[PDB]
Amino acid sequence: QIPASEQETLVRPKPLLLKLLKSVGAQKDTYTMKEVLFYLGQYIMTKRLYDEKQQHIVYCSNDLLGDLFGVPSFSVKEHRKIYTMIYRNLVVV
Ligand SMILES: COc1cc2c(cc1OC(C)C)[C@H](c1ccc(Cl)cc1)N(c1ccc(N(C)C[C@H]3CC[C@H](N4CCN(C)C(=O)C4)CC3)cc1)C(=O)C2
Ligand SMILES: [Cl-]
């Protein structure tokens, strides 16, 4: 399980991630990983990108999120994978 310290990491989103974050209310130059995770969470929730019957699976093949992550789908239970996909879309300060 990922160290709690990682969510305190200061990050600067790349342009596509920044675009997505701004669509869920982001106003900042710099975020914590915790903030990024929560904004992306709200994006998934608001748009209902998760399967109605298999609710842990996020489907994003027809969404900007899929461009960002380079996958058609992923499980929210894949925590290391989620960190990796997010980190590839930002610059650690
Ligand atoms: C601070 O750390 C974290 C914050 C957050 C997450 C992970 C974190 O850390 C880990 C990486 C270690 C993840 C998340 C997942 C991926 C990314 Cl790309 C981004 C965020 N998340 C989140 C997002 C979606 C879902 N989904 C999609 C499943 C439910 C199942 C239950 C379902 N239902 C069942 C029926 N009813 C009646 C309900 O009320 C709820 C709703 C969907 C669950 C959690 C967040 O919100 C914020
Ligand atoms: Cl989209």
Image (cartoon, grey):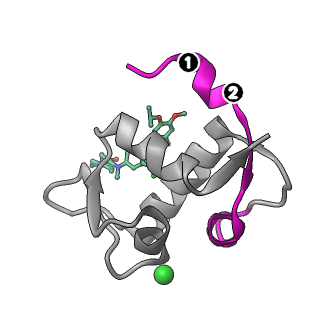
Q: Residue 65 got which mark? A: none
Say whether residue 30 is magenta.
no
Comparing 90 with 19, the one in front is: 90
Q: Residues within 10 Å of mark 1 (few under 14, many from 20)?
A: few
User: Does residue 57 appear to the left or right of 89 in the view shown?
Assistant: left
Q: Are marks 1 and 2 in contact (CB under 8 Å)?
A: yes
Name the spot of residue 89 as percent of width and height, x first. Answer: 59, 57
Q: Quadrant of the N terminus?
A: top left
User: Which quadrant would residue 53 be assigned to in this image?
Assistant: bottom left
Name the spot of residue 5 as percent of width and height, x first. Answer: 62, 18
Q: Which residues are magenta?
A: 1-25
Q: Is residue 59 above or below residue 56?
A: below
Amino acid beneath label 1 = Ala
Q: Residue 4 got which mark? A: 1
User: Does residue 11 appear to the left or right of 7 in the view shown?
Assistant: right
Amino acid beneath label 2 = Glu
Q: Residue 8 got which mark? A: 2
Q: Is residue 14 above or below residue 87?
A: below
Q: Residues within 10 Å of mark 2 (few under 14, many from 20)?
A: few
CA gap between label 1 and label 2 equals: 8 Å
Comparing 31 with 42, the one in front is: 31
Q: Residue shown at 34%/71% (left/top)? A: 60
Q: Ligand 1 within 8 A of label 2's CB?
A: no
Q: Residue shown at 63%/47% (left/top)? A: 36
- SS for tag 2? helix
Comparing 40 with 42, the one in front is: 40
Outermost residue to the left = 53
Name the spot of residue 28 as percent of width and height, x first. Answer: 84, 55
- SS for tag 1? helix
User: Does residue 14 appear to the left or right of 4 in the view shown?
Assistant: right
Name the spot of residue 82 as percent of width and height, x first. Answer: 41, 45
